[PDB]
Length: 168
Ligand SMILES: *CCC(=O)N1CCN2Cc3ccc(-c4c(C)ccc5n[nH]cc45)c(Cl)c3OC[C@@H]2C1
Ligand SMILES: Nc1nc2c(ncn2[C@@H]2O[C@H](COP(=O)(O)OP(=O)(O)O)[C@@H](O)[C@H]2O)c(=O)[nH]1
Ligand SMILES: [Mg+2]
Ligand SMILES: [Mg+2]
Image 1 (cartoon, rainbow, N blue to C red):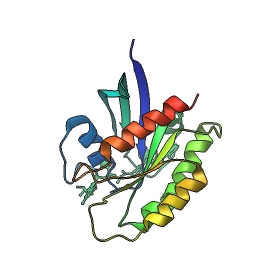
Image 2 (image 1 turned 90 degrees about the vertical axis):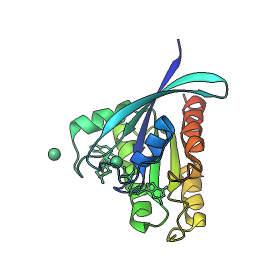
Image 3 (image 1 turned 45 degrees about the horizontal axis):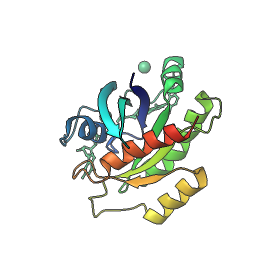
Image 4 (image 1 turned 180 degrees about the vertical axis):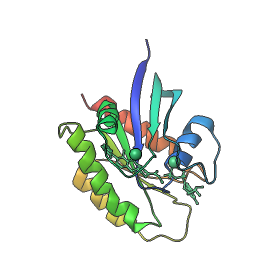
């Protein structure tokens, strides 16, 4: 029957990964969601008229590598690389996330979308230009989002699914 998409949401602590996922799945904003909890969450959506089952891994836990997380990441079909526009370190970290995703997937041209979250905030330290240029270098789309307002949330996950469909 319906197609399942194994999505993974990655990025530095506090960028909005959980707030983004909960918005997509549950349609509300959760301030200060428990930072320890890593889980996968499912939702059926219609995208370009095709019914699809999104299985979304909201990454958390500790800053450590394991063989087990290598294997969970390897099973992911596409990844949202999330930073916050008010957190330059989070944007610098994107490169290291991509490097490790590529390591665990044999350097495949992996479906990835760059996400600049917290776009509602006036305290920007990452210029949109720098994000656009980074996504251009990686050959991936870049979406601006606010989990708080819901701006761009559907576009981020739908674009990733469209990237996975385009890929094979
Ligand atoms: C505030 C907590 C939070 O949301 N975090 C912090 C911990 N963690 C970082 C982290 C580190 C490594 C990896 C990773 C990746 C990207 C690929 C392969 C791999 N094998 N072992 C670990 C690996 C990941 Cl997925 C994460 O997830 C983000 C969270 C964010
Ligand atoms: N203003 C604003 N705050 C956000 C947004 N997304 C998440 N937050 C807040 O940023 C903090 C971290 O979000 P969280 O979802 O826990 O980040 P995660 O660590 O990446 O899972 C929390 O206080 C959230 O309410 C956003 O788009 N705008
Ligand atoms: Mg979280
Ligand atoms: Mg441990």
